[PDB]
Amino acid sequence: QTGIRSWTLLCTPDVTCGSEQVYWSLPDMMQDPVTFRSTSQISNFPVVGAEL
Amino acid sequence: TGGRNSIRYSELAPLFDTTRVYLVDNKSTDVASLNYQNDHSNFLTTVIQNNDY
Amino acid sequence: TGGRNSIRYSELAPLFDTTRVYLVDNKSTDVASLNYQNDHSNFLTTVIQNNDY
Image (cartoon, rainbow over all chains, first blue to last red; front, side, top):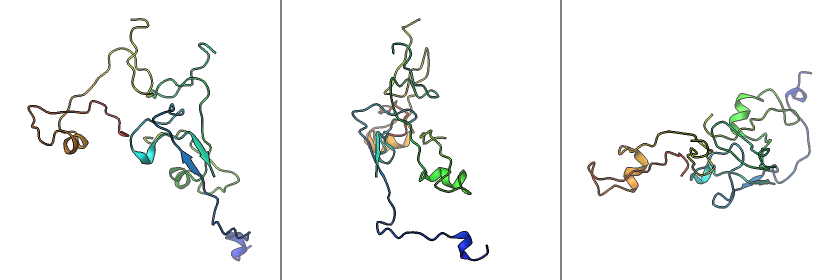
């Protein structure tokens, strides 16, 4: 109730360091999903699909 | 279908028929502000993916 | 009026009846890229005020 056992959690390793996902975007060929704003800033294109 | 499609959002224009909303945790702006005290098994997400709000 | 209003832009949604387009020189992104060799009495402006393109 006081030790590290409190604010931390013991768990399995996983070399990958963390399943992170990626986002596809086909700005020039598919309508921009619901709330996405249309733009030209590569780092903000609309997203059409997510995947690990 | 006909007039029954329209999926609308504030001023951003009419989108028609199926589209996609995303439920994600790792969204940076969210963390800091909403689910600070929460964890991956019970969090809040902003489903509005609009950069300006 | 009826079906004749619709002022449309790429996916950004339907705007209806009068609105406003702006012709401005001092727009920063423009200068650098288009009217470098021009002057205030004859320049180019991007009338699309959308941050992402």
